[PDB]
Amino acid sequence: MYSFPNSFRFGWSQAGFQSEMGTPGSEDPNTDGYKWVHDPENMAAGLVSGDLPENGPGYWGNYKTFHDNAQKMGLKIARLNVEWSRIFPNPLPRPFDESKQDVTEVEINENELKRLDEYANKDALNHYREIFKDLKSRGLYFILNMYHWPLPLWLHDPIRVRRGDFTGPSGWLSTRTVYEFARFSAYIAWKFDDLVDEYSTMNEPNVVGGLGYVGVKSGFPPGYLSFELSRRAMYNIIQAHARAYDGIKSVSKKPVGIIYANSSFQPLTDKDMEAVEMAENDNRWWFFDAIIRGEITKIVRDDLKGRLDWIGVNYYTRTVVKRTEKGYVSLGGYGHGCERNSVSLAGLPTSDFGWEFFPEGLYDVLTKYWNRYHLYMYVTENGIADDADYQRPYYLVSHVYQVHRAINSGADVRGYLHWSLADNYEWASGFSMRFGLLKVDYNTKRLYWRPSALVYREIATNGAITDEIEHLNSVPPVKPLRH
Ligand SMILES: [Cl-]
Ligand SMILES: [Cl-]
Ligand SMILES: [Cl-]
Image (tube, rainbow, N blue to C red):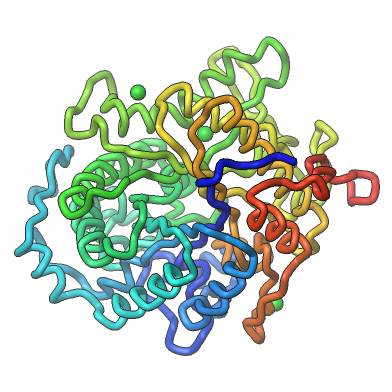
């Protein structure tokens, strides 16, 4: 068997936009995300699937059933977010110099918090309290994340920006968003600190910059192709993280971290190790050096330095790179660039999303983070698009084993949170990509246990990969699968 520390928790992560809607009265029509996925031009272009989040799994109404199943599965930790748009569905009073590039401070005080409170949707706040109270009553440890991509429409009209019009609310291109995010985060901690165990400011901010402004075929808002604006968004997001960290700390003493989308960068050949280092620099270290070391482009900002207590690792697959004349390049046919339901160029099976099976990458990412910064970590996401559940039992046990390995090497990793408990709205892919331990019937909103959920229950209830399931620490046999 492979046993975990007594204090290690197995759990799940989920997102509000992706899981909340689907029961009567649950619709949140007031985000950039909602506008984006309903947009007729985006649908016609096939940038989004045409599936709509309001037909989702219905966590807003059915949370007790989600939590019931989690409890029965032996889970002891959950990471969820509050949707900013639900709390402030209408715009806030303006503050603050918009033309100032750097936001070095955002003052939070009692009177400001009490004024914000006048504009907050109390029905939503109360409902979130009920959800989180139910969660805690199951003996679940609670990581509350503040932001998982959708912004209030009053801060970002993504269709206007897609069209090249920058005269309106521009999301992460505007420092107004930085100011309002810090105040929102402080406000939520002020309201919910009694329920929360740890905080995350954001989920996968690198996706906002990368898919929003470069990987524009992905259907991530606002889909405006610009290296320059991608940089501006990420700069603002970095400052927003620091100001939200300070904001939360002004009302709470609990840990505040951030959650990031990671890949394990792997060399095509033994001569490509330098290309791996460059890729890690360009995709990972620049961001964390900014919020941990205060380093940005080459200076040190004392208002950014030290603004992190823990790191949330989101890991799905690798990225293979090779050296080039000027720098490096990622390769198709490995990692997340494979055919769906096939095999990679390395002979490894791929998921419903075309993502390659590569559990060793999780060890790589965890140990790299540990050796560079020595901040403790949670694996905040790991999972696979697999409606049939063919690969997921292997994917689950294999990745969990790699976390055990990381701990054995000395890395401080305190839990593993699977993405996700149930199937949910996968943004531009709609409902077709099924990441749940539990399968959702979107017509009845019923939840079903895929066999991997029974495997997960064995792990979580024993706090170990038990002898009986050690054989799943292996690659799904490729011969019976599609090539
Ligand atoms: Cl990464
Ligand atoms: Cl450091
Ligand atoms: Cl269905």
